[PDB]
Image: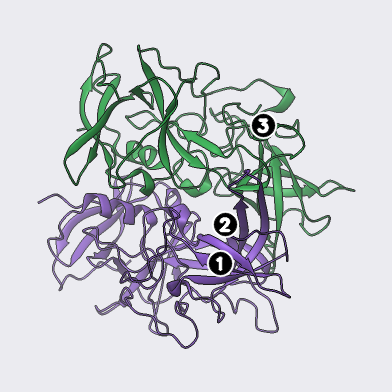
Chain colours: A purple, B green
Amino acid sequence: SKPFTVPILTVEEMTNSRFPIPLEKLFTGPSGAFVVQPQNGRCTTDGVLLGTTQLSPVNICTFRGDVTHIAGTHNYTMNLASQNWNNYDPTEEIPAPLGTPDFVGRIQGMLTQTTRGDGSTRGHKATVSTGDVHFTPKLGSIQFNTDTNNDFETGQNTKFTPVGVVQDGNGAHQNEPQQWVLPSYSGRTGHNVHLAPAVAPTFPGEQLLFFRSTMPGCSGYPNMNLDCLLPQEWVQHFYQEAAPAQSDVALLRFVNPDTGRVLFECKLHKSGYVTVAHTGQHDLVIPPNGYFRFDSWVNQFYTLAPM
Amino acid sequence: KPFTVPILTVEEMTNSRFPIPLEKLFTGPSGAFVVQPQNGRCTTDGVLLGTTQLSPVNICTFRGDVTHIAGTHNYTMNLASQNWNNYDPTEEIPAPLGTPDFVGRIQGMLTQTTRGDGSTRGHKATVSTGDVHFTPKLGSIQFNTDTNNDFETGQNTKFTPVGVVQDGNGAHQNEPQQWVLPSYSGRTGHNVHLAPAVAPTFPGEQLLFFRSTMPGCSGYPNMNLDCLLPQEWVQHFYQEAAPAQSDVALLRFVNPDTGRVLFECKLHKSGYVTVAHTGQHDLVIPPNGYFRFDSWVNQFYTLAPM
């Protein structure tokens, strides 16, 4: 059987699987009080993609299609196409199109468009509110708020490139986005289906280990923390290697190459997430050259050395 | 350690010169211009070259602090490193890693967070990489923005690229110029530490380009963007660091559904691909097709014609 491995990349060399930005740090905390069910950055160790997960880091939270102006507003409806401009297929047993945002919040970026006939182009700042009634990506349509009411043409290829998140209103600082609340992919009365499972520690004294980034902020006082369960590079690695899982738990050691010494160990669960033995919120202190190393498959009863 | 390339399809991979997916393979003659891109440059045994770095999302991004140019909508950015450490202008690279490697106007957004209280702001911005103020190797560049007072000094500021612009007045598709390198030190110095120009010399061979279409944000831009290696190949070689047994790796492009070889190509050790073809051609490939390394060959090996 093909030996299992994880990439030798450092944390700072890797990319968040839930938004197109670099990883910054490792974080652990208790998660009993919310549902950890992200749909991006979901992949089994033997390379089966889950949820809305796809391979391209730059396609996360991007949208493509044609747009139509909503009269009397600066809003546009985007009729979604697939990433390669084929028809979007809503009948696939996935929660939403691959790469769809998996948090409730307002994502700002740019809408860009090319007119096929003459190659004329245009671009405008735009925001999609993934919590609003018009956000129905599973059904094939979403709405953008823009700074124009007449520039975008109908029947022309249009792309949304995400940049960051916004916050405003009378609510408390950092009250949005809500990274652990999935959008309603089929809108307000709809129910999400075909979801990658919720994850939770199941061994005494363990917590999830999160791969954390800080999302760019574009206005107000947003909560910019974004935690993923797997680096995008791990998703890409497992998909290609497709190494058989010899047990349900892979033991990883985090190693300092300058000394060769193990800083901590963690469990990489076959279904695609990581736990450590720790209690409480903690920003991990690591050497920037540190990296993860697979050491062995263990059984369900293995007790981690405290982090 | 056996050399390999990733089993990813073209559409599953990413351009190494701009943060967008690959779309197609293209070959054409390149004698009439200089092919010296600085992003997407890596040896097969994993040595990064030019301004090439590992993150697909950091290509054509900038980070630093900004200062407003009074009476204008322009800002000067004093560059930091990708992790907000001080930028080291003495590093043996042409410019900060991920700096754009073509002359043109790149539009995107500048975003900023105030360290003290977590307030944030964001504005549309354009950087003109052909202008005299574009001196990333010196640690300074200029943006044109849609604000005249909002960005604060001494606060972390990021440029996220989106697409390219062209001035409608003048010939269509006259910019950007993807094969013209910026002057990374402006008029202050010549470019240094460049990945070398590539120019095939084996009879009947052309470069094989990994092509994307850049988003256009205004006017009539040339949106073609050709890279010599997919970003995922850069990432792969860097990690595997498999020894090169010769200067040329023979790859076959295969249809896994049939097992049939569509074409073969040379992956040169210094990091670029050639095919035996003459003329401009959009390759017709099956969507599940992928590249497979078959063997190391020598300087005399003749490819089966594409």
Q: Is residue B16 above or below residue A162?
A: above
Give residue A185's position: percent from left, percent from top.
45, 77
3 and 2 marks on the same chain:
no
Chain letter of mark 2 equals A
Residue at image mark 1? A78
Compute the Cα span from label 1 to label 2.
8 Å
Q: Amino acid under label 2? A: Thr
Quadrant containing the C terminus of chain B is top left
Going by the image, does A2 lie left or right of B132? Answer: left
1 and 2 marks on the same chain:
yes
Q: Residue furthest bottom?
A: A189
Residue at image mark 2? A158
Residue at image mark 3? B174
Give residue B50's position: percent from left, percent from top.
50, 29
Compute the Cα span from label 3 to label 1.
30 Å
Report whether residue B111 is seen: no
Compute the Cα span from label 3 to label 2.
22 Å
Q: Amino acid under label 3? A: Asn
Residue for point 52% across, 37% down: B225
Going by the image, does B220 lie left or right of A7? Answer: right
Cβ–Cβ under 8 Å for marks 1 and 2 = yes
Report whether residue A301 is seen: yes
User: Within 10 angstroms of label 1, few (less than 14), some, or many (20 or more) residues?
Assistant: many
Chain letter of mark 1 equals A
Q: Secondary structure at mark 3?
A: loop
Q: Secondary structure at mark 2?
A: strand
Going by the image, does A279 lie left or right of A219? Answer: left
Q: How many marks?
A: 3
Give residue B272's position: percent from left, percent from top.
39, 27
